[PDB]
Image (cartoon, rainbow over all chains, first blue to last red):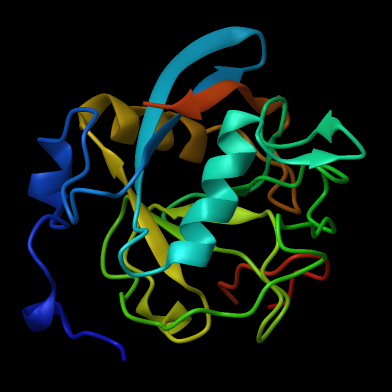
Length: 199
Length: 11
């Protein structure tokens, strides 16, 4: 299923994504969501994200509901509002979305405790892609990462299911990427999704 | 190494 770079669909090059606004580029029915990020107490800006429903519908919908507050447990919404980025590796990726525990151990999806890997269509071919964190095959939950470089060694083990849109989005990713971290790559100052939703 | 796992980060 994995596409080579020469066979990638229109709308997902870095240049194309950086020209993006608030509407999807890969397929017209893909949802666009956002995170407003705080670094410590300071507003860092907005990351807009196209979710590739056309290629990874389950993964896209899971992320979308966690952005909008539509997923509940016994009538209590849970999702990315207030979630942190707990693992940041310069020149590699930024990882977050553990709203369960805030430390990387958390796993919950809108489908249950976990959900299987969808088809591995897209490669980790550049910075600015959204991909699922996991604990091996068929263990997707709530965590994700945004690539800060090509990382094709992750291909066929993590589903690439979205892309950040526009220059501000990437600027925010770069800001997060370069914060000071401890020896375990945890930020010294918290990085939080203070608001999120659908555009 | 350079992985993205959820619980025990490996090399």
